[PDB]
């Protein structure tokens, strides 16, 4: 093991320079199974890694877990092993009424409601996605025929108060986030999730390419509590290889 | 007439939905002359406005002057008159050694070293360009065959201390900005300019499409102070967005 | 030619160490006309410069444009050329009920609602006027007999959201400035403006003397925008010329 | 299931009001084994939960995973199910010369270098542990005879830059965290971890009781990476004094 | 003769003392020193009055701070130079919780930092936390005396009026930051308001000094009955007996 | 016996007074009032010693503030509750500019807000600015007295040691924020360090009260760290005479 957390050596990657990075370890095998020669690499904490082949070239699929801190460990240690391009696939809650459950979202940049991004760049720095990655993700969605939305995502360190949920133990949301959902909605923000700000900032400020795609699992204008994207991200990876 | 600064009516625009927004009033007519049926509309302070036609469709060219404050006035008042798409063309000082004078840069997002962006969105909101605008801009630069870099820009409220210039009256730089250039360079930042953070934040937070393009006029790794394809690029990009 | 934006040399100034700095370029020559031996120096972007003579002493008149960014270029490059004392003349929106259109407002210090002032001093540092410049402006106003108000000014990086104007495209104001005008009013702030915070912070933190004066064109307790007119206020112009005289 | 992530009902807890919350899911079984009638409950994402008994009273053991965001999810959802007292156990890197590998550290409060704590309370509010919980941990430690240090912890959203590690892909650290380890060291800060700031802030501002204990895994005065027990006994003994 | 700029004390004055009790009021010093053996006045300059007394045969200092973090920081710093390593603050306070009664005793584990002087020792993310041994001694000493005691968080404010959301003032207005603040602190479980615990606890914790904080509740801001002078000084005395008794266990 | 909770004064005690001189040292209060007509001791509670005097037939207050903004804010507010509308501060200070001598007098136009109490009245972007009429009277009073006077910006700190970048302390340690800070204020033309002006100036300017600040230099920090009726106390009395 060349790294402290992932349990991987540089030789494990077989010259791979691109990684797909889901949140849930459960999803890693399913993503790799859509490519050639899939083999299990390692599994430690919420970091499950698999190696696959796409058009003759080595590809990594590795999970991040929930949150920026966990994400920052996986990205850093993957970068040490040779990864220069990261493609993020996740799940999300829509906050705009016209976006339906089943729709696919591509993130251009993130509202930094996290702490981990500040460990790489000050708040004035933008949490922006790589242009080539974003293009590839939009072209892939277009070829597959998925109903897709491009724009800004709010990336939060919490599931509950930072996304202004009141259905909680305290039923309370601190001053900073009181009335914040209505504010993001007016600013044209598409959705909430919990990892992109960290991923995007840390890659953009360190010479690493990153992209972000996600499937909608809930619409917050209706409820607080609740496939194509998987095909989109692997198709995008083919154009970036 | 309809607006306080620009001196324009909705009728002056004749249906225009897109605007090209340079900084210098003197470049406004030059950009308009590259398109069909160029007509001068008005001229007040920083704001010189022209109407032209591109593929039979009305287009506005309006100057912003230097800085986010005056840019925010032009953008706001054009939006009241019906503009929904804004394209900035400017000039810039590169901070990466591999970028030469005359190269073209396309901004995906800006480092917010301004004050006016905060009047539209809190600091954690990204100063990000619209994707369709950026695509057109990158595809236009490639069609004309320009040497092109795509990435992040540092957008500063000042020409001197905020860009870490020491050849000044005082010769000093405040704590915040001392050592900041080396820091931006290490973070992959391409260039310094003075307007993008304001333009990009106020558009992305109000449902307005915005893109940013600039020609390199100086490189900071050698000196503090010093037809371009940039103008051809912005006009070709505007064509694709109408 | 000695500077990058203003297109001037030290020779153009002919020994000048005081400059009057209006916002609008079209005001430069009109201000210069009230003084002896006026001549046009240069004009680039929003920097229009004229030289005049007051009691046999060389004085510069140079525009700044709208906003602190272009103000900071003008003030810096003028300082490089030899200017050590700056007097700003502008227009303003009053936020107190008793202040009338055409009243003259002299600023002691400014609420830093700008970004450029942070490029010279951290937010703790006061955006304060020079005492000698303020004295000259106050004493000059009394000599003219204008209705004068002295106090704090809020200096915003925007005309619209930062001055809590709602009649806009979005009709929306961000959390920070929502309810802000009522708060400044209660705190005794006289007016809204867009350049003083940058100017005063620049000069005070770099050993330069600065004064700030402006004439009211709208009262924000009744309307956001002044009514349009056709006919072609000047009190503040006389006051700023007379104040310079007392400073030379 | 009564909660969204954990996959637990109120009936699963059997009236439990106290939870031991390790970082690593692997530890859940081991901590539960030291108590009686231990049984598995659920496992979803980084949240593995067990239930046991201590002096005839039900106790929960539930993992949080790495970081404040994940910690905040577990703590909130356990609170909805009835948990009022939280005792965290983790691993940590020491930054004081007089603190060695294998020593046990009890946190009174944390330096807030996270983002999740701000979602509960503004920065001025202290990430402070409950006094009853801290007392139980200190006293449990002295009865086992472990080398114990009591004080402030640095709680970071990152393992690398925020803890000022330079053996990285970029080799640089951002302005804010550059020269920061030396500063914390002069301030009397004991150690580095990643979850206590979030945990202590969200409990102290919501009427919940919380304590924090960890074992020293690396000394940062001599090395960045560790490689080149007592705490588990202490946390179980502390919980026993809290029921 | 003085070893320090403000306090007017020497190391000889201390007689080898390593603990100090640090109240706010100059006039309270003599009264607290009256609960110990053989008290003698040492000095009195500005708001800083100092006395020495014996406790179980050990030298102890009692020295006032004045109101606020700035004057507290001067006193604590200059005492530390003279050789003091442990500081125990006794105060009076206003409770903001309905279940906390006038006459109750409050021990602070840590403080909400609404001061400016703590920032001169550590940035805002550092906790304004009490020393464990000092808090242990205070909680246990409270049981010896028999007080009704609450242990938790305290809001430490640089002002008595607007920072404690008081509206009965000259202006009658409260700045944006503090408008609605009392209600929010109440929800977060904050017990009370005072004016110096944030400075003291931050400056000691970040400099290798031990500090503790105890106070008696003189008023509650949720109820309408305001106690008289006699009942208030009865509460103060009750909390004063706890700080001396806690000091015994810290020698 | 008292209309206010800290000072121990009634509105009646002020006898119509609308101006107060507000020094820092309680012991110094009596000596200032002794320079005026019919001085009478009023009260003494905590760090607040108050005396009443007369100047050209008008009642004036001299009241002690104690050290620091918090203590200052209590005095100003309760004095305001009893009718005082004009405050004049007289203090001692440490100069940080080479050209300023020990014994010189400094009039403050505005302060660097290195405090916490000012934020309880106005956000940080609000200027800690003195009243123009008060500053004028102080500047003119200096001429009449005949002292060497400098007018400008003052750094107003919540501490005496770390915030004034002093290293001769127990820890010998200065926090990141204030590391190298004295050299920075110096280059920004800041005259001096004190501990009360930011709170005083901000709270008065944002509440419709008039305030002024004068001080005598007791030490120069470019030569020395620790220091060791004056001109400044004469100037504050003369200024008060001009503002009645
Ligand atoms: O509202 C939502 C719904 C889902 N997600 C998101 N917000 O946070 C992301 C977490 O990693 C994880 C938490 O369920 O899934 C993503
Ligand atoms: O280094 C540079 C060079 C050029 N520019 C930029 N920074 O600021 C932009 C100004 O609006 C304008 C005036 O400098 O030109 C752009
Ligand atoms: O309400 C107002 C009215 C006028 N002004 C002010 N606010 O901003 C100043 C700008 O420079 C310019 C913008 O019109 O004029 C000054
Ligand atoms: O230096 C260290 C060493 C260990 N830990 C800490 N920092 O972060 C904690 C993480 O949860 C997890 C990361 O390995 O373990 C804790
Ligand atoms: O509500 C209150 C009541 C009392 N105190 C507190 N808040 O502030 C403390 C001051 O030092 C001093 C001011 O009364 O006493 C403490
Ligand atoms: O450097 C200095 C010197 C003196 N002073 C000042 N700073 O702080 C003021 C304190 O109230 C008091 C404490 O010395 O005196 C004022």
Image (tube, coloured by chain):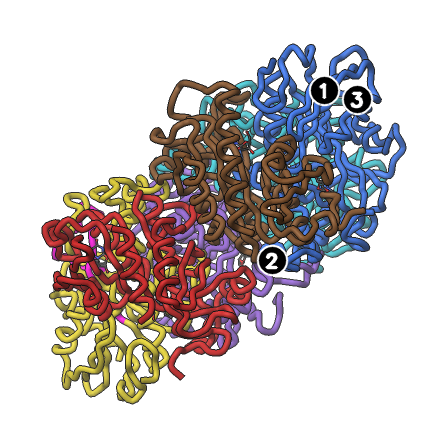
Chain colours: A yellow, B purple, C cyan, D red, E brown, F blue
Based on the picture, tell me whether residue D171 belongs to the magenta stretch: no
Residue B151 in sight? yes
Q: Do circles 3 and 2 both sit on a common chain?
A: no
Residue B56, placed above or below residue D172: above
**B18 relative to F67 in the view: left or right:** left
Q: In this orientation, which residue lies closer to the viewer: E35 or F79?
A: E35
Question: Callout 2: few (<14), some (14-19), or many (20+) C-alpha neighbours within 10 Å?
Answer: some
What residue does disc 1 label?
A: F61
Disc 1 element? strand
Image position, residue A181 (x, y; %):
28, 44
**E20 relative to D193 in the view: left or right:** right
Badge 1 sits on which subunit?
Answer: F
- The residue mark sitting in front, 2 or 1, is 1
What residue does disc 3 label?
A: F33
Q: Could you give the CA–CA distance between mark 2 and mark 1, rounded to whole angstroms?
A: 43 Å
Image position, residue F93 (x, y; %):
76, 42
Identify the disc placed on residue B175: 2
**B211 relative to F65 in the view: left or right:** left
Q: Quadrant of the C terminus of chain B?
A: bottom left
**D135 relative to F93 in the view: left or right:** left
């Amino acid at each position: 093991s060349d790294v402290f957390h992932l349990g991987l050596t540089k030789n494990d990657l077989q010259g791979a320079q691109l990684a797909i990075v889901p949140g849930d370890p459960e999803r890693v095998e399913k993503i790799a199974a859509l490519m050639d020669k899939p083999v299990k690499l390692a599994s430690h904490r919420e970091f499950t890694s698999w190696r696959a082949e796409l058009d003759g070239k080595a590809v990594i699929v590795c999970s991040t877990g929930i949150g920026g801190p966990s994400t920052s460990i996986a990205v850093e240690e993957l970068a040490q092993l040779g990864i220069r391009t990261f493609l993020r696939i996740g799940t999300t809650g829509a906050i705009q009424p016209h976006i339906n459950v089943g729709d696919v979202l591509v993130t251009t940049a993130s509202v930094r409601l996290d702490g981990a991004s500040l460990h790489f760049a000050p708040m004035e720095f933008p949490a922006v996605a790589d242009f080539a990655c974003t293009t590839a993700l939009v072209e892939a969605a277009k070829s597959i025929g998925a109903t897709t939305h491009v724009g800004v995502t709010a990336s939060s360190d919490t599931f509950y108060p930072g996304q202004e949920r009141y259905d909680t133990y305290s039923g309370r949301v601190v001053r900073r986030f009181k009335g914040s959902m209505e504010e993001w909605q007016a600013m044209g923000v598409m959705n909430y999730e919990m990892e992109s700000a960290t991923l995007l900032t840390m890659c953009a400020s360190q010479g690493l390419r990153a992209g972000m795609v996600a499937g909608v699992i809930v619409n917050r204008t209706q409820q607080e509590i609740p496939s194509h994207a998987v095909k989109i991200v692997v198709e995008a990876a083919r154009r970036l290889l």
